[PDB]
Image 1 (cartoon, rainbow, N blue to C red):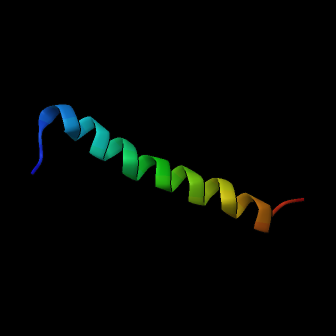
Image 2: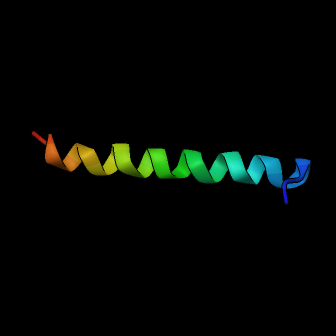
Image 3: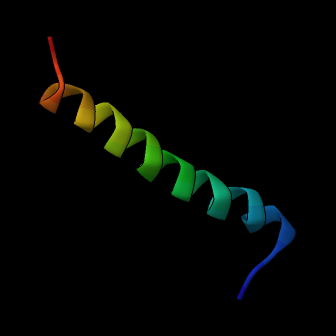
Length: 31
């Protein structure tokens, strides 16, 4: 089930995962 109110939440959830991966990947390429 998808809703407009939850629509933002759904997008946010995916975005958070992307940020985490990007942030995590930073350690791998850390300086």
